[PDB]
Length: 291
Length: 290
Ligand SMILES: NC(=O)c1ccc[n+]([C@@H]2O[C@H](COP(=O)([O-])OP(=O)(O)OC[C@H]3O[C@@H](n4cnc5c(N)ncnc54)[C@H](O)[C@@H]3O)[C@@H](O)[C@H]2O)c1
Ligand SMILES: NC(=O)c1ccc[n+]([C@@H]2O[C@H](COP(=O)([O-])OP(=O)(O)OC[C@H]3O[C@@H](n4cnc5c(N)ncnc54)[C@H](O)[C@@H]3O)[C@@H](O)[C@H]2O)c1
Ligand SMILES: C[C@@H](CCC(=O)O)C(=O)O
Image 1 (cartoon, rainbow over the protein chains, first blue to last red):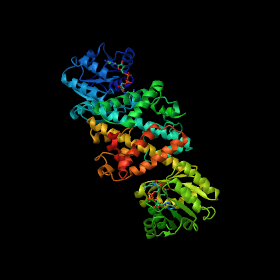
Image 2: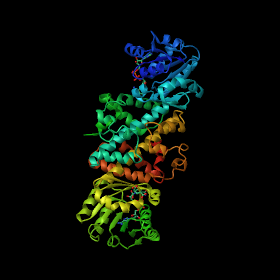
Image 3: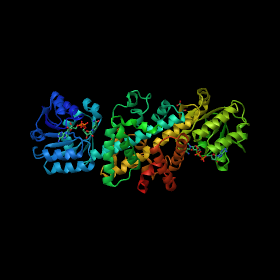
Image 4: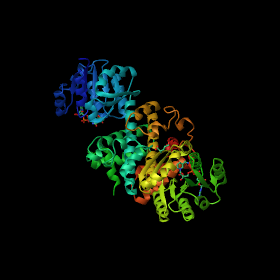
């Protein structure tokens, strides 16, 4: 065994992430207050503990993979004094840039190294060890973190100072939401103009409007058989998750005083769509555009 | 092949020169003397009226500003044309006007394509224009030898109107992507994320598109992008505003819902009132107006 890693949050992402660490030869000290999550992690080789302070107590690294910034803040407030001095904390939760910098500052005030390393790839990315880690913090701290991150990761990219990981991801996902609606709008307009879906696909994908939202995640069935449109809009990337990321994008915009017209319009659209269609893929927003 | 070329402006001139360069007999007409003179300089036999230029032609190409002008041109010249003369409209006009002129042309025993272009004056001179073609496939096959000399890319979009539909749908997406990318870069700046960091991430992730990887609206990440060169077009706000207007005509006509597309249209219409002469990526610096 190489490093002793505490993992806090063994959910849909945390469990397959923790399993890959166990496979790579690490001792993984898990905690999750949902007992079903803890059991599933235990089955794949994680040492499950009674409380989060117990898990972090004998750990060289501490990964958190949690729902929100409020949960990360409270987790940190609980566990930081329990951890040994100069333990490496890695938050791979998707939280706000304001929260990330608060919890980063908190971790350093307790004498701990701290990175924000939010991920893209979903549960499939998590299990196959192909997640993109977008890291913020010190360059030396990331260098120390790499042997832990590499067995979970397809790509590791340093974004800047603390919170830059969260900033990088939330800017990209804001763009992605806008693209996904914009592509849906185009396909529906083509439909009404008598332009075939296959033809619009071939044009856009060979021209300047090409992007992942069309080439991989095509919102009409046919042109890309692997896309969610061909499987009843089963995620994939859920509307619930995109709505959450767009909430954090709107938080970032509100915090900075920025102006993002189309990003905010996309946030308003997905917020309404999430109310009734949270369980569908975010490409399904196309359904709002048909009378 | 003898070719009538009607509209010898910024696009029509270099296109016609390329056809002369490929061994075609190009007959021309433009109501601007400077346009006609400069066309005559590179081998086009200019004529005093459009019906005159059309008379001895196997093919008739229009590169004109609007649908009203293409419609009027067609009615001025269709009687002067021989039967089975191939008409190609490379003007960018609405899908409604495109299908109207197609029907009108084929009623006179002509073969007609809509075939608008992407690539600008740069692509027109270099002969790398992307023709997106609506019409019959056998009519496109006949058109290929004429199109090849002006084109780097030729794509059959469908029946009459599909060419105009395909272009306007893609450029609507482009306008939205260009603004979305510009929002991402100023949000990143205010969050203390460098331009180069944001560029590296987005270009290797789901958000990647031409609007960032080639037309990056901040200077540095892509040295050749207009942002590094006082926002010299490139692809102007004036022309993007022109293409979005046509998208809104299409949305109005079909009764389509296109909120982001329509929002991009409003932004660029307002932006074109101040900065029509700048590249459409310059929209980044008019965001604080909203
Ligand atoms: N699933 C995806 O598609 C996806 C993709 C990218 C990013 N993310 C992000 O990853 C994060 C987690 O995602 P998930 O799908 O695993 O969420 P999840 O709800 O499945 O898992 C979160 C887990 O954290 C546990 N938890 C709560 N408080 C805790 C504490 N104090 N200590 C230890 N554990 C605690 C919960 O019981 C739960 O099991 C989220 O922030 C999400 O935005 C998810
Ligand atoms: N310039 C570009 O970057 C570009 C790129 C792609 C497509 N387009 C499209 O191509 C079309 C024309 O582009 P342009 O840049 O050459 O415009 P332009 O204004 O430079 O040229 C149009 C020419 O047509 C002439 N004209 C007007 N009425 C006429 C008639 N009845 N018969 C013959 N000629 C007539 C005008 O005098 C003018 O010289 C437009 O619809 C535009 O949207 C332009
Ligand atoms: C558009 C056509 C011709 C290209 C060219 O002439 O360079 C082709 O690519 O097949």
